[PDB]
Image 1 (cartoon, rainbow, N blue to C red):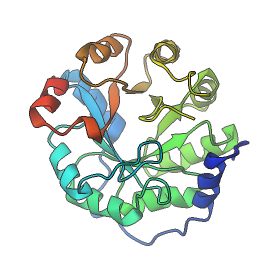
Image 2: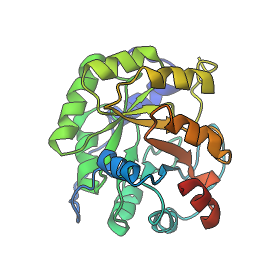
Image 3: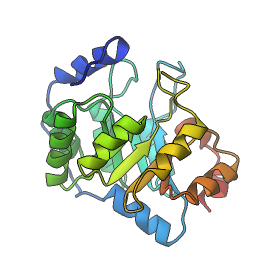
Image 4: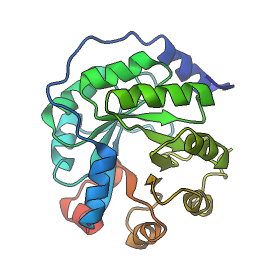
Length: 250
């Protein structure tokens, strides 16, 4: 992986030594990028529900993962499950349990640094994974992207700046996420103004995911929609009331 230091390079090598898992999916892949485009054709607001048990930035407990997934299943275009163990309190069993009880695209949100994690994701039932360009070399990101595609998994590529986006687009990325739920570490670089900037630099063909900032004003959403954003990544902690989810969903 690229030159990382501090907190991130730690969880990065934690992933490198993460023991592979033996399991087998009990349902095939349900494509996330493709389900978003169909949500688009029908003008359904495509919301990827972002779920983590605990977080380092915001130290707060969560509600039952299985119960939450069963709930969001009728609304979200897909679910993003944080499987990192140390800082985010996720686990592979949690992912396997969610992928078994739900029939909508599941995205494994973790720090993928080797092909076995991708095998892990496929075998645990995830429908795709998160690939972070700012963590992998252009070499590793091209390879991993191919590995996942062989499984039939079109990964969502996280980019945080024009640099990451150049790397991603040249290796042929077809599914991209401008920013994530939390606002980076270099942080002011991560704002609403830079986000539209990065979005306009993405080819109309690419499926674009925008990490929303403020959920409630629908005119941040229907505005990003006009700039081509296909789906929105939203923290679970802002989607608990069904009627409110509907207000977002139209």
